[PDB]
Image (cartoon, rainbow, N blue to C red; front, side, top):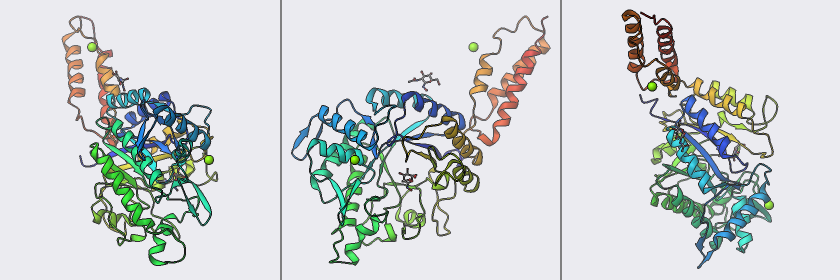
Length: 433
Ligand SMILES: CC(=O)N[C@H]1/C(=N/O)O[C@H](CO)[C@@H](O)[C@@H]1O
Ligand SMILES: CC(=O)N[C@H]1/C(=N/O)O[C@H](CO)[C@@H](O)[C@@H]1O
Ligand SMILES: [Mg+2]
Ligand SMILES: [Mg+2]
C-alpha cells in the first residue's frame, strides 16, 4: 500500500516544443492505462507555450497590456523555436486538458521555468521594452537566464509566475518553478559556482551576492505559489549547491525534483542533505531521461536505448546522490525532453519508455481495471432463459470480478485478467433451457 500510494509521473517538455491537446490527451490515456498518477507538463521551458485569456501583468509601477504580453510571448517563443505544429495552448485547451486528466484520475503538474530556461520570457520582456533582462558573464550574454540584479525583469517574472499560479489554483496540487541550470549557456554549465564565487573570491568580478539573491528569488516564488494553495517544486541542482548552507536557507515547502547527482566540477547537494534540511523529494533520476529524436544507442546523451537501460537498472527507489542514506520519496518521475525541438515526436517511443518504467517498478503502478469494467458491461443482463447451473456459474464469475481488491498493482494484473477470462468462459457456456 505504501508503494501504490506514491506518485508515478510522466514528464513532457511542451516548453521547447509544441504538443497538441490531442497528443497530450493520448499521453494521459497511456499514463492512466499503465498505472501512473500524474502528467508533469512543462509549458515554460526555454519556449513558453501556454497563454491565459488575460495575460495583463502589473509590475514596475504599470500594467503591461494583455494583448501586448501575448504578442510578446508568442514572438519570444518563436524566436527560440518557431514550431510549425503550433505555438501555444490556450486557456480553454488547458482547462479542458486538466478536466480530461481529472476524469481519468490523473493530476497535472505544470512547470513555468525561471530564472534559467526562460528564453521566451526574456524575449517577451524585451519586446515589452524592459531593458537588459539577460544575465551576462564576462561579456557572454545568456539567452536563457534573467539577471537577478535587474529589478524590473525580476518583478515582471514574479508577476508572471503569480498570474499562472492563480490560474492553476484549485485545479492542480503542485507547481514546478524549475530553478535548474542557472546561466548554463553563458557560463559553460558552471552557473551555481559563478553565483557563489564572489563570497569566496572577491574583487575578481563575480556577481555580488549572486547566490544569496538566488535564494531570495527561489523563496519569493515559493511564497507566491504557496499563497495560491499550491505546493512549489523545483529541480535540485541549485539548491544548496556545493552543499553550501552559508548563503541562506531554502523554503522547506519546496518539493525537490531530484534529477541529477551532478558531474565533474558540478557538485550538487546530496539527496541526503536535502532530506535532512526538511525537503520532500520526487525522484526524477536522469537515468530514465529520453530526448526526442535520439532514438537508439549512439545517437547521443539520453537516447532512448540509454533511457530504457536506465529504467531496467535503476529502480524508482534509487535517488541520485544518496551518500548511502535511505532517502524517502514521494514518488518517481520519468521525463521526456525536446532539447532539439525540431525532432519528430514519436508517440510509440514515448509510450515504450512509459511502459518500461511501469513494468520495471510494477508493484508501484496501479493495475488496469478498464477491461474488467467493460467485461461486466458485456454480460447479458437477463439470465432467465438459461439453465440454473449455467446461470449460477456466470453469477459466481461476476462476483469474483466485483470482489477483486480495488488496489492491485501492475504486478498483479494477471489476477484481473484471469477473472475476466473466467467470466467470458461462463458467459459462453450459458445454455438455453
Ligand atoms: C472533460 C472530459 O472530456 N471528460 C471525459 C473524460 N476525460 O478523461 O473521459 C471520461 C471517460 O474515461 C469521460 O466520461 C469524461 O466525460
Ligand atoms: C532538470 C533538467 O533535466 N534540465 C535539463 C537537462 N540537463 O542535463 O537535461 C534535459 C535533457 O537533456 C534537458 O531537456 C533539461 O532542460
Ligand atoms: Mg533569441
Ligand atoms: Mg449494463
